[PDB]
Length: 460
Ligand SMILES: Nc1ncnc2c1ncn2[C@@H]1O[C@H](COP(=O)(O)OP(=O)(O)NP(=O)(O)O)[C@@H](O)[C@H]1O
Ligand SMILES: [Mg+2]
Ligand SMILES: [Mg+2]
Image (tube, rainbow, N blue to C red):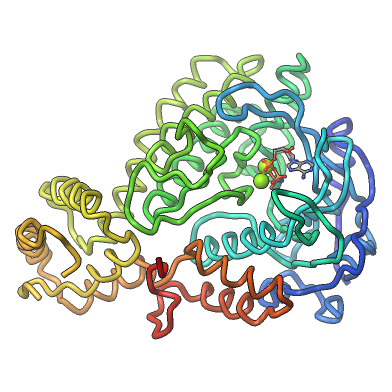
């Protein structure tokens, strides 16, 4: 009753190795995404480790591991690839969409280099929570369908339980796929990937009547829009290597990510990123640098001129999306030219006071235009900014009430803070999944107000 196609396998020969998952020892299902399963037509009986542990294949699957390469922290890293994951198959939905089923933690692969081919419970829990949180914030992302843990030791800085995440996404194409064949000097394979992407994900483009310029122009726009959305909610990816950039503009590969607590533009959550390359405030520039690396691979068959014109459009797209999202977050229903100074003055203040990002915006969503009605060392500077902020609000001539409702629909009450995830992980390792299930539920409603500790700052 589920329909898998062998599209990648049949259309992109020599981009993968066929092979099967390696099962863990005493694997067992600890969580699965019941809502998403209903959307994908997966019978609920399939969840009672089976395919979620890579111990069974469903009819139509033909598992392979993809090859790719990448720049890592700005330096060419050579061959990478699906070193600890496997594309089990591609499921076609009634929508006509296809959805990759990718098993992360599936065992050793020809692409594992010196890696064990395994993922650990804590990283699979964090990735499931992050990708579902992102999805309910309305930001493009891969999705999490299931987690299995095991009794199989996996050694990181300490011994951890081996685990696997069943990841679901429209595609796993990365900028690094193109880079891989470009630097191997196989420009034909580069173009094969472009044509495949256009055929299956930009089919409204008529074949070669400007298809390549228009497609890459959309690729830029989707990455700019993705970054704009991360910035707005205070998400720091932390490992924006070119192999972790999704061609479609999906958030891809959750590792040492971080949603901001205290507002700090130079926030680094990846403690291996010693130069702060992937600090929060560099994500706009880094994503442009990554697009330029992708643009490098297409110069054999796309005019270097059209490539730079598409690269040129990046900062206007990003600024359009960011500006429209911020105006909503500040409750600006119209657009006055006071807006950029009020913003710049807010972010300057928030930074000096180390204000919590999410909480500040959610509290600002209670503002009443005519009232002056506490978290700042310099209350003098706040009430002066708040004063000029509320005066500009009155210019909208819209009610206290509908501004508040607009803001509450774009400023979440809850984000996936590191200490909420940690708490679910600690409980999970002890065999209590209740916290994990409770937190996943809460993240399906980020814009709804809460009474519990899911909306508090971390305890310190
Ligand atoms: N434990 C591991 N064993 C084998 N390969 C690994 C391991 N950890 C990372 N790699 C590979 O090292 C490269 C960089 O890792 P990373 O960007 O973190 O990807 P990943 O989290 O393993 N998989 P993904 O979410 O598909 O991008 C990729 O080729 C990974 O497949
Ligand atoms: Mg990766
Ligand atoms: Mg990773």
